[PDB]
Image 1 (cartoon, rainbow, N blue to C red):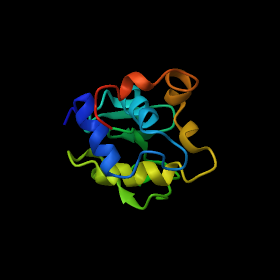
Image 2 (image 1 turned 45 degrees about the vertical axis):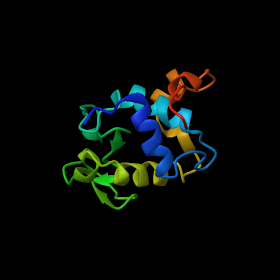
Image 3 (image 1 turned 120 degrees about the vertical axis):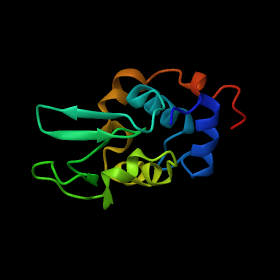
Image 4 (image 1 turned 135 degrees about the horizontal axis):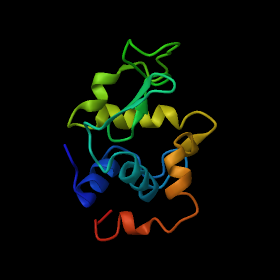
Length: 130
């Protein structure tokens, strides 16, 4: 499913993402925008290390979800990577929460550092009523 901007904003708010571990909704929106373009079936294979990023938040199979084919993998979030490809983003939200429960926080995603960090991210939630 490809979410519309405001539709995603409200869904994430309802999931308790606004301010989770100090991360504003606008930041989670910025991350989703650049990681997947708000697309839940987005998958990206990393040939270099044989891991795959899954879903709207591009969650990595090496540490957060289990896909069985990733070398030296762990299942920190304790989920099947399949769960991060559903239209319902509840599991993706719970996984994203687990990722940021580590000291790096939102910085775990390098795309966040490149396009979101130290930027005016208000544009991601403007007009959405959140």
